[PDB]
Amino acid sequence: IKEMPQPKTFGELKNLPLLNTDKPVQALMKIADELGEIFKFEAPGRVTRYLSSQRLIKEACDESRFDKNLSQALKFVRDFAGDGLFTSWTHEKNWKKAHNILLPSFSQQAMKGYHAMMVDIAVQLVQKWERLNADEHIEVPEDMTRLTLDTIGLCGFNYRFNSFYRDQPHPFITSMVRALDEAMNKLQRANPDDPAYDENKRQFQEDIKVMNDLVDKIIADRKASGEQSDDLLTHMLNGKDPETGEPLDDENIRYQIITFLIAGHETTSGLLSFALYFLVKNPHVLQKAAEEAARVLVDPVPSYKQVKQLKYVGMVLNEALRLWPTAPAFSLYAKEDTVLGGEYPLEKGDELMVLIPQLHRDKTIWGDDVEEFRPERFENPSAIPQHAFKPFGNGQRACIGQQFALHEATLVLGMMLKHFDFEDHTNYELDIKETLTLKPEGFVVKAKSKKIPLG
Ligand SMILES: CC(C)C1=CC2=CC[C@@H]3[C@](C)(CCC[C@@]3(C)C(=O)N[C@@H](Cc3c[nH]c4ccccc34)C(=O)O)[C@H]2CC1
Image (cartoon, rainbow, N blue to C red; front, side, top):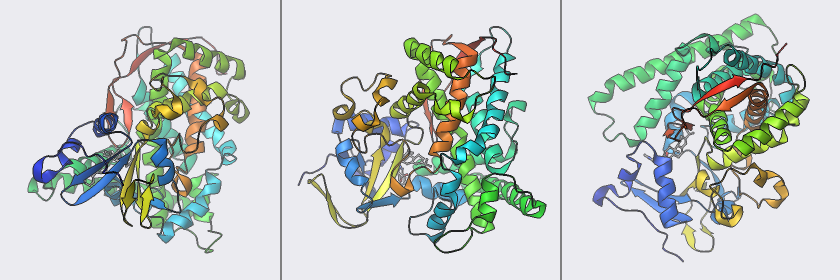
């Protein structure tokens, strides 16, 4: 057996102070560089092991040996996402029921139906950019977040956040962003029962209240209406689990819509923000992506068929997902006593953190140029070893939204490369802000129209 490495210690507090930082994933990536494919992490009441190699993670991805664990991050989000699919244990009845009912709604076939609604928000973004005055710049994450939140709103619940009509975000979103921020702040908050956080707790309960009232209202209205809008809310009110014959209740539907609205905010827009960033830093890659867009997107508004044809744009999103996965870690627990890589023995209940950005830089898999933006790496999926590329997590607890997120990102990116030339006018220096997700903070561009009509 190997004694696995541990990073620097702080007497009683062990390693806890290393997560007392505004960029913990990046801090943890630098520790991985030093310590390698596994290190232990202790804190007063807990212990976790961080994996970085395809070698160890491919075993952790064995669902017969490891199941999804709720991280302290997920337990904190659970306070408003409840037993939604994202913050439920594999063994909760509402996980499997909601999973069986919703999978058909998130299928690559179901994308045919969402396409029109997605095109409606993508067109809103293109027109915003066509209507900019000369020398006016684009705030990339902010406009990408407008598109992604509006798209999950419209396609899911037939609800228009109308993000391209406002400076200040919708009220639901104000409360959701503040709630997610409270949840992320609680991780490194020592003495959280101190009365200084009474305004945090009071505000937290209000933000929860806002989210529940607005979503429960959406759900009440829809049932009272009787309208059969082809969308997630409809599928969830009419759906029945093949296994147990039961439908989701109204409270659990709410949790799913809250989970979807979290997922489709900065988590999804992150992918577009990192993609456009990599594209403008790598002009020969942008040029090739734009040539595909122009060749494939011959109609004034793209069809579902043409999006499937944007293969190089698909490879660009995968390569952005390799370097900066916007849900950068997920937690597993050993279902039984077991041995990882023949070296490190684990007792039943032991937790693993998978460090996805570090997996994606494993040079044994990707070779020596792992820091380079080469979409060509993804030309053949059969040449890529098992469990090498995990931006969407693993097995039955993988991202149900993967097809939706990739379809919207392919459509939108395609339309952006067809309609505009891009300028990195500030020569932007990457600064990755860490919240519940990752985003290139302050990332700005200019977009010259090619003056191609949408009509
Ligand atoms: C909501 C979803 C998308 C998220 C999942 C996450 C999982 C791992 C997280 C995360 C990336 C945020 C930063 C801490 C980190 C890396 C983590 O190890 N956290 C461990 C260990 C830990 C850190 N601080 C703690 C305080 C108490 C207990 C455990 C911890 C944990 O959350 O459990 C975080 C992002 C948000």
